[PDB]
Image (cartoon, rainbow, N blue to C red):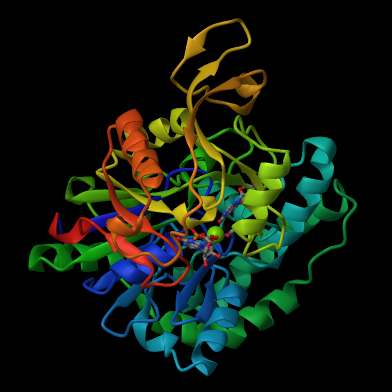
Length: 431
Ligand SMILES: Nc1nc2c(ncn2[C@@H]2O[C@H](COP(=O)(O)OP(=O)(O)O)[C@@H](O)[C@H]2O)c(=O)[nH]1
Ligand SMILES: O=c1[nH]cnc2c1ncn2[C@@H]1O[C@H](COP(=O)(O)O)[C@@H](O)[C@H]1O
Ligand SMILES: O=CN(O)CC(=O)O
Ligand SMILES: [Mg+2]
């Protein structure tokens, strides 16, 4: 179909960046619809590495116009940082990036608050990325937050900012006993780049409506993952935006009836960064092996990611929540050499029940134990393989099994971090 959504079906870091960069070869637009610079992606073209955060993963292609929808919480500082980085490398961001006037702005006091609140929580700290996402979403929802559209009137923005900062500073110093964040500093920093920012502003809703009528291939790119969703994730150990497919319409302005194919990025094993339930988490040698072989360290905070087996019970939650059309299995190559691979097929509740559905809030996950199916692993190298025939039968079985257990076809298989090390069995666009 024309409108294809690409999002994470686990806890983020499944390989969205690469897959979006690969697939956008036929796309006209690429849209970020939620999150902020909390995300981190690594694209790799012929060995050249690119780490993105706020900017969409279709920025390396000139034929594509990258858009960051209203659902995104925009950090002026963060954007500029990535802009210069990409520009010095020959990628003209200003020319291929459009942004929404509705996008809320992430200013310094948000990071201060984020750190403050995270400290206050103490032992039950969420383990947030420390980029001010939560507080940004908060001001938005409260209706006191600033959006890109405010910047258009430098006078009143300065005024509006003045009061909001008084507001936050009061609690920052009084309640949290933390240092105040200087207004003038925020005003100067922000004013220093306003003209650049405002130049990329477009009416993205109306635009996507127009693109739709023309039949333009559009790709929506999700940040984070399903189980990190504000409503449906392992609350409160989640991010403050709807990471699920429903965030596409709220976060871009496109009517929900116009989603043709939701491609779910599924990693061959699981990882999670930050606090929260993780039924299949491995603390043993295999965990170390997985972490090591998959270079599992957060591309935004550098933090070592928690690792574990693929959880089909949890993945099945992503299926229904996102209305998955197909899966893209990433990192199959990381399992090379394992004597055996296991996939969680059911949960054993703390009261004795065997269930194949997921608990909601984090608390209700507390004594939940995983029930596995153990399949033989494979010694053969699958790295860089671009054809199923190069895959050992075990790997093929592992693949068939996942499809069986989920009811969703694995339409794409990734065998390496490079754009070309992939197998496209069915293209979301012409399917
Ligand atoms: N071995 C291997 N590495 C991969 C593959 N796909 C992606 N990677 C790398 O694995 C990581 C995926 O994590 P991350 O970048 O945070 O994913 P994202 O946030 O969903 O875009 C990145 O460092 C990629 O460069 C794959 O198929 N195999
Ligand atoms: O892009 C991401 N990838 C993986 N984990 C993330 C990402 N963004 C946030 N998190 C996690 O989401 C939770 C809340 O963090 P926040 O979004 O920084 O406020 C923490 O568990 C973070 O580690
Ligand atoms: O790509 C995002 N990271 O893995 C999150 C982090 O660095 O905490
Ligand atoms: Mg990431």
